[PDB]
Length: 456
Ligand code: SRM
Ligand code: SF4
Ligand SMILES: [C-]#N
Ligand SMILES: [K+]
Image (cartoon, rainbow, N blue to C red; front, side, top):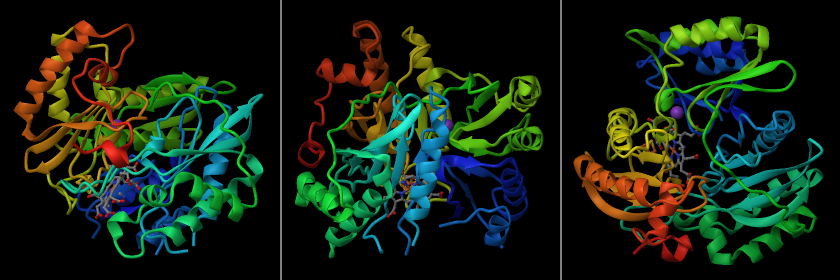
């Protein structure tokens, strides 16, 4: 197991070929696994640092996890600056010993593809005239829980305020050091920032950040999100450039019989003009394709099975690695997701909602890597073949789903969904998501204050 530090998920075609070769020759699994934090992992490594270092890459005492950046913004021009900032925060944060891991993101509204509420520190980009002017700071997200331990909880990030672009690094350092100093000195399960904020209070933590940073936050500037999914297919970028986002199930890049996914990405890597962008949804964007090159790239991606059409449901579903490589795994996730969604697709079709989607995620244990705690329907592994079923999150990812059923099996999960999806398909309002519906319809109580009302 090796994971790369790759701010914003941007990787060159040169870097890609070097990782493709290594994955294939020097690992047990021979795969490249894109993670939901915009980076990649090798599994079963049998030198990697020299191979990484040779292409200008590095694997991260350091609790600083990969800094994410919205991968394919609607306002395409904003990416360059937001990305430059994710990269600056990432290096600025490189070695203070943190009590727990620290996760940071740079978000470009209206997209919350990076799932900001699962992170400790978030910089929401505010732009004027196509130029970034500052960031709204949101602090305190974290999804990890421990089964039956009501002292642990998933929490959403809290708004601190707006800061001019110039104070970015000072504010970033201040949040880190304040967490480092105030974090729980005894217990490791209560050391995350989300726990610190609840103990001292947002205003107290905020006041300290201002004092340490040497600034006063300004009122939050308006922002809103419309979704968290990738933009599968071709989208028009700036100039005559196009972006082709490819759906990769579980982000597992391997050559399969008749679906040479891995070779396919290598062939594209060799002819692609720009770079690739690994998304927070475990997908891959072939970025900066000149309009003249669209046909070449598309032919390869099509032949390799990279563009096999899936349902919108499959595109908005996610799972963590889990077995066979994870030692903390309790139930299957990655290996369970495909056929599970096969079942969900049937249910969506049965109800006349094959064109709809429910943000559905499966995490193999309560650590929550699959981000099921921010999904509309989250499955949280409890034992082999058993999961806690959580409902009530929303499409944008700003609400934690409450546990609806505990330690149940797939046939039990499917039966419950068959019933709920049917009520949704028939009772929902115009454009109402599944999650919101279960809350409006009284199927599940919403989680309004995670630290206090997440657990029943
Ligand atoms: C690959 C990935 C899941 C995926 O399918 O994409 C993953 C994989 C692992 N996670 Fe994670 N986590 C991944 C995103 C996250 C997320 C979601 C996110 O960050 O967007 C969470 C939930 C949010 C949060 O942090 O609160 C997450 C919370 C955990 C935890 C709980 C940490 C905590 O604060 O309690 C652990 C275990 C630990 O560190 O104690 C962990 C541990 C692990 C390890 C490294 C197991 C271990 O400790 O040895 C898993 C490796 C499994 C394997 O065999 O590859 N993983 N993990 C993601 C790698 C991210 C990255 O590239 O850096
Ligand atoms: S949620 Fe649990 S099983 Fe899944 S990858 Fe993370 S640690 Fe492993
Ligand atoms: C998980 N890291
Ligand atoms: K994916």
